[PDB]
Amino acid sequence: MVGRRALIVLAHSERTSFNYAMKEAAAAALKKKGWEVVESDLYAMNFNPIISRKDITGKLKDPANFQYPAESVLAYKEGHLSPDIVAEQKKLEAADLVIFQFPLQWFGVPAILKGWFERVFIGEFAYTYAAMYDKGPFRSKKAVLSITTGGSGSMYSLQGIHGDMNVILWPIQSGILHFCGFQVLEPQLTYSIGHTPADARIQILEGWKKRLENIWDETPLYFAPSSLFDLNFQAGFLMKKEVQDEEKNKKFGLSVGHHLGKSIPTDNQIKAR
Amino acid sequence: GPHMVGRRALIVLAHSERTSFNYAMKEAAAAALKKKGWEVVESDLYAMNFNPIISRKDITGKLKDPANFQYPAESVLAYKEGHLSPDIVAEQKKLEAADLVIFQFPLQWFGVPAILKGWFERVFIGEFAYTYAAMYDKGPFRSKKAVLSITTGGSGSMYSLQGIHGDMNVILWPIQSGILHFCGFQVLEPQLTYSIGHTPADARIQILEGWKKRLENIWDETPLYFAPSSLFDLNFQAGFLMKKEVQDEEKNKKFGLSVGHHLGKSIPTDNQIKAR
Ligand SMILES: Cc1cc2nc3c(=O)[nH]c(=O)nc-3n(C[C@H](O)[C@H](O)[C@H](O)COP(=O)(O)OP(=O)(O)OC[C@H]3O[C@@H](n4cnc5c(N)ncnc54)[C@H](O)[C@@H]3O)c2cc1C
Ligand SMILES: Cc1cc2nc3c(=O)[nH]c(=O)nc-3n(C[C@H](O)[C@H](O)[C@H](O)COP(=O)(O)OP(=O)(O)OC[C@H]3O[C@@H](n4cnc5c(N)ncnc54)[C@H](O)[C@@H]3O)c2cc1C
């Protein structure tokens, strides 16, 4: 009910960027509230984002038919993961709150951050088909995305040329974060930061600092509870028969991905209900 | 269907293993197109040991503003001056030549592998791949066709409307619309190979044969539906919003236009998976 440890993952090469200023603003605001703040500035760490056989520090189980998921899980169980992955996994294990600070790039996370998820979020460590989504290993943790874009807010509105931002956010927030157990908080969306005058930029930094004063007390984003599904291969991980019947009486879909051919609830991936 | 002899294909592969089904699919695609007279070029990102990280090392000469580095403006300027790193230039020349672009990858964390995401970031430079002046429909790759050939760990049912992962059409949207279509590409129906780890040996053989059979007449296919850019007022003053007349015509519709342009309505079935 009180958050004490935070991890800030930053994905920007420039110490001069607004992204770096947002990482500094976050670290300062949380430290003032008594949090222990740990950082993963991917570029300053020269983080290797590419999965490979070298992520296993020893012999492989089946090198003739190398399969990264089974091999990396085995290396995790045996303590044979590459020390750079182990150090990141320790940061995650200690954190209550995880902040991801990054510029939106090609409607997703920068490649360096994509590879950080790929090499760090190893099976059993971060996810398991035995405890999916709300039952996941990171269920006691909270995650938040703080994103800057080149495009304006209107471009990402329902009627905007790029389409709904809620759709762009879904694969990261549900698929990457929520699948691992994280309760996902409302994203900090900083639109067209390149076309924002100096006065407003100072205020964006202060607004983010003020939000972080009570971040742990916020209501997280709504995702469909895992209890609504038959979480086993035989049923095909499909929504329960009774839930399918009950949902026929629902006007809106449960979320973006669980729209069910119905209207998506307004800002399902942007605002808590 | 119509002959494509001498036409050009680029296969971008994102898998390190020669023994992978992804590599098998790349080989099947190259053999099928070559049999139809296509000129086939590949970008095996792991074999190339492709640098996937955007940095100032992507520009060879002097920068416009080295104390305040901004990748978009610096990379565009480098493209205009022909000062992009040679590895980027070699990939941009492969794309320029290609009529058809196949992206062969295993689905990783509900998107493209980091190496392929890095390829998009370093290769798809402004002016070369996109402009705010000619977004989406009018984009530089409007004469080209792109196709995703994806393999997944999860079954088809996990990615169905009622599946635990949610609708696959939503996962596909940021790649197909945001990356490919924004650049002008006509996007073809994705080749989706679900739970390839659970597929029996005879079924895996027939997935390869089915892919080869599809590539025999791929250029003749109807592309996926995206809302035309002509429905929007493409400028800052209008905020790149749908035209008033389009908004009025949409009020009594039950269905939205696409995944991204769902407009608070019902998404048409398989908008990112099946063409109309
Ligand atoms: C590969 C690539 C792909 C992209 N794809 C997309 C896409 O899909 N969608 C999209 O919308 N955009 C896209 N973009 C644009 C991108 O999201 C923006 O360029 C980015 O968000 C800008 O954020 P920044 O941190 O780099 O800011 P900067 O450009 O570095 O900074 C913005 C301003 O803030 C100022 N600033 C810095 N520090 C401070 C401080 N302490 N206090 C106040 N002001 C400060 C700077 O001086 C500058 O004036 C893409 C960019 C790249 C490189
Ligand atoms: C970091 C990471 C994240 C992931 N995230 C996700 C996710 O978000 N969603 C998801 O659903 N999955 C996810 N996965 C799973 C991933 O999509 C699968 O592991 C992958 O698609 C398997 O395809 P492959 O090419 O590696 O095949 P392999 O596992 O290498 O092989 C599959 C089968 O094909 C056989 N085969 C190979 N060549 C031939 C041939 N010529 N003819 C016939 N059979 C052949 C093999 O022997 C094997 O039986 C993730 C995996 C990783 C590494």
Image (spheres, coloured by chain):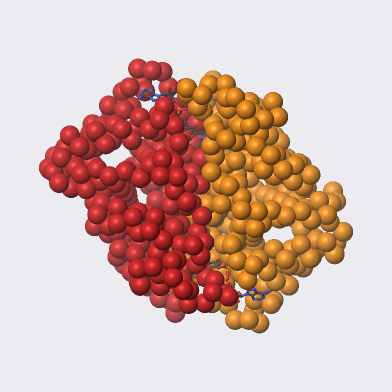
Chain colours: A orange, B red
Percent of width and height locating residue A231? 60, 27
Residue at 63% of width from left, 35% of height from top?
Answer: A122
Between B84 and A41, the one lying in front of the other is B84
Residue at 71% of width from left, 36% of height from top?
Answer: A137
- Along the horizontal axis of the image, is B227 left or right of A68? left
Percent of width and height locating residue B136? 35, 62
Counting the numbered discs, the total is 0
In the rendered image, the vertical position of residue B65 relative to residue A35, given as above or below: below
Percent of width and height locating residue B238? 43, 76
Q: Quadrant of residue A179?
A: top right
Between B228 and A101, the one lying in front of the other is A101
Percent of width and height locating residue B251? 41, 62
Between B234 and B15, the one lying in front of the other is B15
Res B214 seen here: no
Q: Indicate the quadrant of ligand 1 in the picture.
A: bottom right
Between B186 and A229, the one lying in front of the other is B186
Residue at 48% of width from left, 77% of height from top?
Answer: B64
Q: Quadrant of residue A23?
A: bottom right
Residue farthest to the right, as pictured: A34
- Along the horizontal axis of the image, is A72 left or right of A30? left
In the rendered image, the vertical position of residue A86 relative to residue A8, given as above or below: above
Residue farthest to the front, as pictured: B61
Res A24 seen here: yes
